[PDB]
Amino acid sequence: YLRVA
Amino acid sequence: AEEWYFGKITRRESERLLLNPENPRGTFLVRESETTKGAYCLSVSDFDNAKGLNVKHYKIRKLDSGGFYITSRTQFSSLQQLVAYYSKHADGLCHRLTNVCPT
């Protein structure tokens, strides 16, 4: 899953 | 709003469905997570000029209270509100949600 923020 | 929710399909099938070369950039679907039981996933097609077609997967987490979030900065009371927000705002995602994934 991607890392966000 | 149904159409974009594919329920219990696997990362591999979502990728089969999203990597369809006909699909524009930002084509998406929402499914349940395989790895994190009780969580969801936002799966979205993208493109790199050098590498081509690829799929980004974002885990949609659910608080105990009932809310949903990809980032704790922006929380939502329903998955339909999360989809409607990222259709208008990329706000951290690779790209804004454009197309609903076919079939």
Image (cartoon, coloured by chain):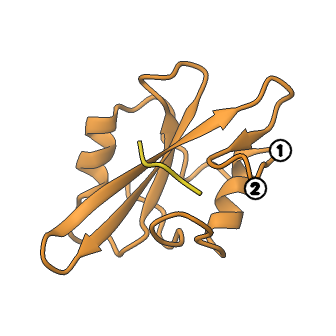
Chain colours: A yellow, B orange
Element marked by disc 2: helix
Point 72% across, 40% down: residue = B68
Q: Is residue B80 left or right of residue B20?
A: right
Q: Is residue B2 left or right of residue B8?
A: right
**In this orientation, which residue lies closer to the viewer: B72 or B20?**
B72
Q: Quadrant of residue B91?
A: bottom right
* Residue that protrudes farthest toward the bottom in the picture: B49
Residue B2 badge: none
Point 42% across, 65% down: residue = B27
- Residue B30: x and y in percent read 52, 46
Number of residues whose C-alpha sits closer than 10 Å to that of mark 1, classed few (under 14), some (14–19) or many (20 or more): some
- Residue B75: x and y in percent read 78, 49
Residue B81 badge: 2
Element marked by disc 1: loop
Chain bearing tag 1 is B
**In this orientation, which residue lies closer to the viewer: B4 or B70?**
B70
Residue B77 badge: 1
CB under 8 Å between discs 1 and 2: yes
- Residue B7: x and y in percent read 51, 34
Q: Quadrant of residue B22?
A: bottom left
Q: Is residue B26 left or right of residue B64?
A: left
Q: Amino acid at mark 1?
A: Ser
Is residue B91 positioned above or below B43 on the image?
Answer: below
Point 47% across, 70% down: residue = B99
- Residue B78: x and y in percent read 77, 44
* Residue that protrudes farthest toward the left in the picture: B50
* Residue that protrudes farthest toward the right in the picture: B65
